[PDB]
Length: 271
Ligand SMILES: [Cl-]
Ligand SMILES: [Mg+2]
Image (cartoon, rainbow, N blue to C red; front, side):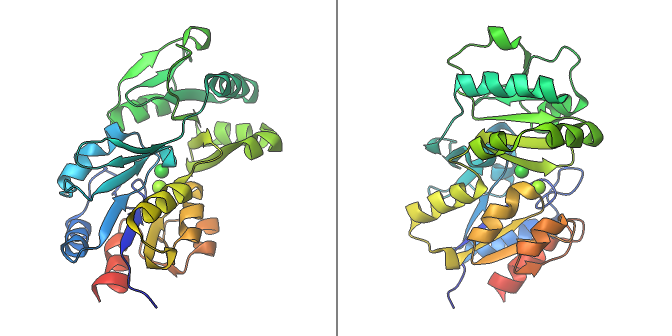
């Protein structure tokens, strides 16, 4: 066996309590693993705007600290947010997916490196949620007035769960082949370029750093975490994970409410 050198950790439902804080147990386990030289990388659907305050809270400011944001469409240096890898959707892909959302009956919003956009005039509660909780500015703009050179890192279909699940059932299987289409919560569907996901993001960084899959632990809760939990040598699901994520995990740890991230770090790293 090999020791763990990198821990990839999802944020919502996994690192963070429901009030969006990091418990003292989880902050102390992450500090103990980084004091030993183990690299810890927050690996999330969120935009960077929703990550950089937590990087500073976790003292992820050293030259060898990274984060993976926008569901793997962006890999960054944590000290200053600079880009290490990017793959964006095109403008034609934005217009196709914006129209698809109106056919299948879901609200929709798009993100670039700094801003959250929607063409919905009745703005979903879950677009206000993303703007407020991920601390990212919100701009209303009609689809046909969007700048065609916007750099579309990810888009999302967001809605009440019953509306979003009805919408998912109406998406043709071809679209699910053409793009990365994965839920991150009952009310969020993440959509990005098919070349990128959290698994590709973790593998990109592991190859930059000379770290084998065997030396990686990944921790998550929802459908958009399955590929990184399968790629890692130690794939971990919190107890509040959906069933399909527990199925592919090596280990099911405690819920986020009971500090499952700290318990996993103690099991595979600190002990
Ligand atoms: Cl996520
Ligand atoms: Mg999550």
